[PDB]
Image (cartoon, rainbow, N blue to C red):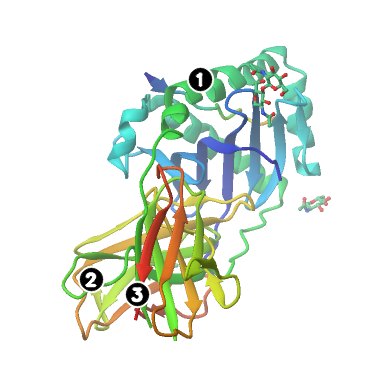
Amino acid sequence: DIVADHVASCGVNLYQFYGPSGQYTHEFDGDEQFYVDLERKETAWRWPEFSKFGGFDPQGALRNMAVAKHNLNIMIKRYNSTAATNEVPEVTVFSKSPVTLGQPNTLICLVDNIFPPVVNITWLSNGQSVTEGVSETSFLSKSDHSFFKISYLTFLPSADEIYDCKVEHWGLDQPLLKHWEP
Amino acid sequence: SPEDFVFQFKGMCYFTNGTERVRLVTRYIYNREEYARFDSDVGVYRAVTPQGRPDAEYWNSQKEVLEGTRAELDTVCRHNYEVAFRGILQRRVEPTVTISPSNLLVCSVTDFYPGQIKVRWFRNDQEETAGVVSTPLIRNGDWTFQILVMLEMTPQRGDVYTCHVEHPSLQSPITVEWRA
Amino acid sequence: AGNHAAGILTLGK
Ligand SMILES: *[C@@H]1O[C@H](CO)[C@@H](O[C@@H]2O[C@H](CO)[C@@H](O)[C@H](O)[C@H]2NC(C)=O)[C@H](O)[C@H]1NC(C)=O
Ligand SMILES: *[C@@H]1O[C@H](CO)[C@@H](O)[C@H](O)[C@H]1NC(C)=O
């Protein structure tokens, strides 16, 4: 690798045949500075605090995606149509801060070693899917060109809570349920 | 079976010593294999694997392409450092430090930024190295880290256990005391 | 006050 005090990705351009779909983000020291909503054609911030560190003009990202789609078709033929290897992701679930009964917390589900970047991350409360209070990062890049993604669930800790993070991925024979143990 | 074909382009800026050393590396990647690269220290494109030889030769033969990528060291890396990264590098989030028992003592150091931290355990003002288990640094993804440091404990009466946390945001290290 | 970004080139061959 390259030794350096700080690394920025300006940007991470992802484009995949499946979908097809693209993703445009800038990263700094491994965290997501901003993304571009490719459908609305608008720069956006998962973490709005970081919008005070400059905007971004989105047409450059959309031009990149057009070229990325073009380049991908070329590389698929260069590599005689060799599809992506489905890696086995690695899932871990933890809380943002120490758990205190009745004090709002955040459950964090880290899905690491993701490739290809095609994944379903869902939260289960007492074995049932939960949509309220859920958010997630973009596919965040790694120097081995795999990805990780993190999902969040805000919740009020209780004595008989039952939470799982459920991950579906072609690298898994069956959906992986990772139980949260306080 | 379902399958995917992935193209990635990474415009990566490496900074050392503030702005003293700046290095642009653009990477062209099929699936997980980087096949072509521009490295500003080299100054021309290189084929990382055979499948990138067409593109290196094609790009290196066009003066306008070469000048355009070389310029990005200034117009992207040095530019975004002044616009964004200088300020981001001044951002400080002070860690929350808490001790809770479970014998084992658990020092939770949560919600801090940036990542550089040192968590030490003391018993009666003496540093404890043995029986200490520290997690790796934990990236929360929301621009904070956490780290958990457990200490194996056999308390005598009158014992004071201190968790000692040094972090760039702190004027002086945070000490949290615990006694049975 | 805008961030800039590296451009993706179209390939050869
Ligand atoms: C980070 O960059 C600065 C600026 O070049 C370095 O400071 C210089 O170091 C030499 C040797 O100590 C001195 O003779 C110069 O007078 C310094 N320049 C200034 C403006 O003060 C600093 O050493 C750098 N750090 C590292 C690890 O390379
Ligand atoms: C994720 O959910 C979608 C819903 O359309 C489903 O079709 C797809 O098979 C799931 N993805 C994986 C990797 O299982």
Residue at image position (65%, 38%) is A4
The reply to whether discs 3 and 1 touch (Cβ–Cβ < 8 Å) is: no
Q: Amino acid at mark 1?
A: His
Residue that numbered label 1 is attached to: B79
Give the secondary structure at mark 1. Answer: helix
Residue that numbered label 2 is attached to: A130
2 or 3: mark nearer the eye: 3
Across and down, in percent, residue B62 comes to 72, 16
Q: Specify the quadrant of the image occupied by residue A161.
A: bottom left
- Asked if badge 3 and badge 1 are on a common chain, one would say yes
Across and down, in percent, residue A149 comes to 44, 58
**Callout 2: CB less than 8 Å from ligand 2:** no
Q: Is residue A47 left or right of residue B40?
A: left
Residue that numbered label 3 is attached to: B100
Q: Chain of mark 3?
A: B
Q: Amino acid at mark 2?
A: Val
The reply to whether discs 2 and 1 touch (Cβ–Cβ < 8 Å) is: no
Ligand 2 quadrant assignment: bottom left
Across and down, in percent, residue B3 comes to 55, 62
Q: Chain of mark 1?
A: B
Residue at image position (79%, 35%) is B53
